[PDB]
Length: 189
Length: 178
Length: 14
Ligand SMILES: *[C@@H]1O[C@H](CO)[C@@H](O)[C@H](O)[C@H]1NC(C)=O
Image (cartoon, rainbow over all chains, first blue to last red; front, side):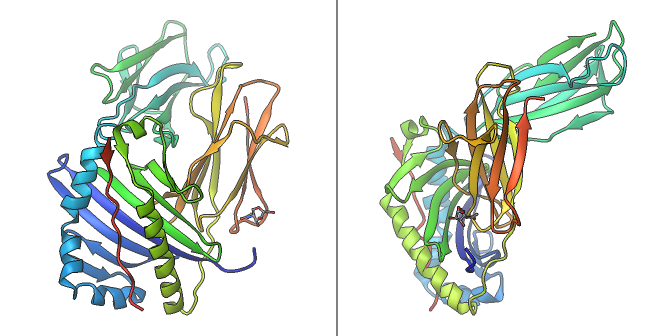
């Protein structure tokens, strides 16, 4: 299509700290690619982000009811919806599967990369360390960062640059909220 | 910390909006406009929770309203297209002849309109596939996920084919074992 | 078994 496009995008946000002790609610409105007007719980009133949203910041902020309702969203909207989502979202935990393979580096004793594949886990907080004979490799780590699979799982790869020589043992050590003691997979040359 | 976002949008002249809930960057559910019903991202989400679909179709109608308002108010400024970044990968490391899934990750784009297509060995695969609605990003843009369940093999190659207005030609992203 | 709350949002000025 050759025609132009016009995009209205309202976003209602709930931000939670210390579980649910501190909540912050934002009602944000985006015309095409700019934010026009916003409500911020920590501010207490609507506030025009750009010129386009001044007519509205001004009208709201005048109706006691619009403001009352807004200010009372941390309770009637955010906290309540936490109460629901909590079981299968905040408390959702899924343990990672952890492979250690070399990255097509079949050579006997040249430069290689050791892949620590870590897939299928939730939430996203995870830590992946490499150990050579019980000592923690801290240099030469080519990570992919977190990778949201979009199905409520993640994956990640941390690759170790090494020249393997017979008798060396590399260990990949994965920590994640879904397991008590760290998960490990080793690799021997 | 955690974030729950109720994300709606409405797009003209296409007359198509979306209503969804988003937790730490994953879709909790969306509302199927066509069928006016709730759609959970994972079926067992339906077992702990519920949502009345009508109330969303109201919010969209109000969003249609405010779009036309804010469009007039803006002297009919249109949106700058932002072509997507595309990436193909698999949800778990590959093991030949053992089922897996190809993930097409369309990121960092707007407006929320693309055409995605899976091509096994050049032909389009229309069976087995699923997609996610446009997930909000923080920078006012969108991300989307297309899924092809597939059987890894040395005799097969695949491409994800994305078509966006901010793109010159269609974008092919390639994947083959090795 | 539990119900989620949408937020009806505001009307822009016209
Ligand atoms: C999607 O499919 C066809 C392409 O021939 C058409 O309806 C439309 O222009 C396409 N939209 C795109 C590429 O954004």
